Image (spheres, coloured by chain):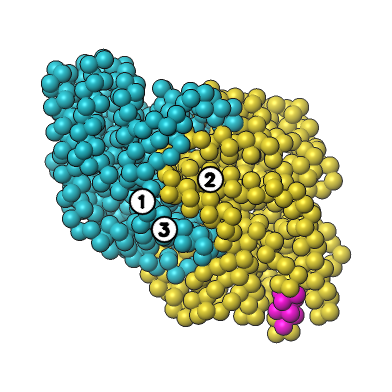
Chain colours: A yellow, B cyan
């Protein structure tokens, strides 16, 4: 059984899962035996349609052979030597072609690593130390950015961090231009970087308000602060060239992962030659014995090569998302359950609202959205859905990540499963 | 050409390599086209015997099919879902079986990640903040440990670190029991952890002095400080159960990577249930979307499964190292070049000179410009090792007698050109 098999896992993995968040993501136990397309198989041989999809990398679904095969070939030809390799130029060139604001990169194993070195690059380059974040925006778990009352409160996110960890890190509310302007008027000249999820995906899928990214680019440019887009989720997802392209605003540095490597552990950060100058001279720092290994860069080449070869991909993904959005709206409407749904392409939040919530609200930030949401009922809904054979994360603020494997028929099954689950609510 | 192909790489990879250290590791350009066994193939189709081997993971050489095949099978069956998986228990159990001081683990993508979370666990568990390191010991590049690289001076290792990064990190010289005793007599009660390379591999291969690890275990135990063995390099390398087993001293936490995943990006940290209690309750923190992904844990299961099935492996690896050691000594003796060589199994340091117990003592004997010159010459003869004398060689089962005999010839020829 799932529950018994999870208990077995817990006797050797402290907490049941390596990541503290993802260990609370299966309150009705589910242990995977295999996966393909958008389908999981249980250790009880149950089939589950996955709307979470391993948190963003799988644009084409699980077990994508066009990418498996390339990575497996690399295992047969040397996957990790630590030396420069012919692939390094091909990976770099693909990223540069597809991403406007990137001409050079360095690779890492994870978004967390890529962010930490990107922030260091901004501090080293500007000779400043102060970094600005937004509430609910997640940039991995490195010591200077790991945050958990006002949105300007900076609260450490983990036990066992040094007390000064966040001394040079500051926070504002998402989509609050007045607050942002006031900050820059006071401290624009001390800011090394503003880091931001151009679309906030780790706390609902709150897109930026009209003009907000433009405003950020202006203030940062005027003040000499580097603008860092964390596109770990949005890159190669909301458009071929990420949110950068979709919203027509170019940052100084860009962090990438997820879709880039199709699920292989790999990330990068980069920008134009000017922003990357201290790394071109090897004066600034980045490291990691596995960084840019040959298997990882084969995965980038195969995945970005595949995406490049499909010039109408993002149009079809958009139809997929629209159809899921329309279907899920009908199912909740028919049941007379208020719901909030935000979508940017195949990135999608679905949250069940309180009976006392304003159905027509368009929250612009995490606090506004959280307040409308009925968390206990949503948790209860996802247990029910999981039993009906559909998995999404129990926290309403955690997004769904659709894929080309979520065809019309799949989405029609999802509808049925959600309908049945709501009736049990 | 190698040089032209590297220049192409540098137009899109800032600095030519993603890691700031490994971008200075090929001053005579070498770009890889393919690799297998202990052999590299150039973009000019040259063959090079690799003594560096990608910095530790490849105990059986490059392109190990018994491990390729398992990982490729995982790609066909779902490699990354973010959910608990049947493999998780098998990977955990294999580590627990092979490593004395580990009963539970969490996985990470890299030694740097695994270290950071391990140190946080020790701070959270003890309610203390102060961490002790040793000079020349490398624990990755996280904010609270990245030092440059007196022995007591704590110097930041990267530009753009917050100024307070190392405020709660302290350093002593390796193998200095007096200093270590004095530290603990004064501050034993404030120390959250002592982190240490049980064999110092990133600065020569300086093993611990007789009784030093035993002393560390006693002081940390007495003071309630967690002893953290960074076995990223030594684990499954110097013995099946790492330096832990080899030297009979058990730490509170162990960090693992490298050999564990056979070159797949994967790491872990773990200990006995007591030391891992705040992670069992999910009160302490670790994260990363790719942590413990199915491909990574398939690699751990295949690699550790293979090692487990070969109970005399570490004895054969010892013969391999002895033969390399004896051969290299003869070649330098015959040429009348003084050399310092330290070895622990297949971990091996070879430095050209102008028994040190620490980095300062060893560095002082070494002729760095001549060693750099020697490695350019060796590389041209078809043997690659890192140009810095303090960076170790990582031998493998693919370094057979014939290979080592070729290495001898190539080193002889290179010394004559010195
Ligand atoms: C925008 C963004 C992220 O979303 C991000 C990681 N996000 C997630 C990590 C989770 C985890 O570690 O278990 C789980 C997911 O819920 C989440 O999106 C990271 C950190 O990446 P990584 O997990 O590879 O360290 C950086 N930037
Ligand atoms: C002992 C030790 N620990 C940790 C690391 C860091 O692991 P990674 O390079 O995967 O971050 C290294 C790299 O040289 C190492 O030698």
Q: Would you say the magenta stretch is mainly helix, strand or loop?
A: helix
Q: Which residues are magenta?
A: A412-420
Is A344 situated left or right of A260 in this image? right
* Residue A230 found in image quarter: top right
Residue B146 seen from this side:
no
Is B238 situated left or right of A147 in this image? left
Is B127 situated left or right of A63 in this image? left
Q: Are marks 1 and 2 on the same chain?
A: no
Tell which of B213 and A252 is nearer to you. A252
Q: Label 2, label 3: how many angstroms apart (C-alpha)?
A: 17 Å
Q: Is residue B126 magenta?
A: no
Q: Label 1, label 2: how many angstroms apart (C-alpha)?
A: 18 Å
Q: Measured from the top left, where is residue A242 in percent x and y?
A: 72, 45
Residue bearing mark 3: B69
Q: Are marks 3 and 1 on the same chain?
A: yes
Is B320 situated left or right of A33 in this image? left
Residue bearing mark 2: A298
Q: Which mark is residue A245?
A: none
């Amino acid at each position: 059984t799932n529950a018994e098999s999870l208990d077995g896992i817990k006797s050797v993995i402290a907490g049941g899962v390596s990541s503290s968040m993802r260990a609370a993501a299966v309150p009705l136990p589910l242990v995977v035996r295999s996966a393909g397309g958008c389908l999981l198989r249980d250790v009880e041989d149950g089939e589950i349609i996955d709307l979470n999809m391993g948190y963003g990398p799988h644009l084409f679904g699980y077990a994508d052979r066009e990418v498996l095969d390339a990575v497996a070939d690399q295992f047969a030809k040397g996957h990790m030597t630590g030396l420069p390799h012919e692939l390094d130029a091909r990976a770099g060139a693909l990223i540069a072609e597809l991403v406007p604001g990137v001409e050079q990169v360095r690779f890492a194993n994870s978004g967390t690593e890529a962010v930490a070195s990107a922030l260091r690059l901004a501090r080293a380059t500007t000779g400043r130390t102060l970094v600005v974040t937004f509430e609910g925006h997640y940039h991995g778990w490195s010591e200077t950015v790991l945050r958990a009352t006002r949105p300007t409160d900076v609260v450490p996110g983990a036990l066992g961090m040094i007390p000064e960890a966040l001394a040079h890190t500051v926070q504002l509310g998402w989509n609050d231009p007045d607050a942002l302007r006031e900050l820059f008027a006071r401290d624009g000249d001390r800011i090394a970087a503003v880091i931001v999820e151009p679309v906030l995906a780790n706390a609902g899928v709150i897109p930026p308000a009209p003009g907000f990214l433009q405003l950020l680019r202006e203030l940062t440019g005027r003040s000499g602060a580097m603008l860092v887009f964390d596109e770990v989720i949005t890159g190669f997802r909301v458009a071929r060239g990420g949110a950068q392209e979709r919203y027509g605003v170019e940052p100084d540095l860009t962090v990438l992962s997820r879709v880039m490597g199709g699920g292989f552990p790999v990330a990068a950060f980069g920008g134009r030659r000017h922003a990357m100058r201290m790394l071109a001279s090897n004066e600034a720092h980045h490291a990691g014995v596995y960084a840019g290994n040959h298997a990882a860069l084969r995965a980038v080449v195969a995945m970005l090569g595949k995406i490049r070869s499909l010039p109408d991909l993002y149009e079809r993904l958009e139809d997929t998302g629209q159809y899921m959005e329309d279907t899920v709206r009908e199912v909740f409407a028919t049941e007379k359950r208020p719901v909030h749904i935000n979508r940017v392409g195949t990135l999608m939040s679905v949250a069940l609202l309180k009976g006392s919530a304003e159905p027509s609200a368009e929250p612009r930030d995490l606090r506004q959205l959280a307040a409308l949401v009925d968390f206990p009922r949503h948790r209860r809904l996802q247990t029910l859905a999981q039993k009906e054979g559909v998995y999404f994360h129990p926290n309403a603020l955690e997004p769904w990540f659709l894929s080309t494997a979520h065809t019309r028929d799949v989405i029609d099954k999802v509808a049925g499963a959600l309908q049945r689950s709501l009736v049990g609510l």
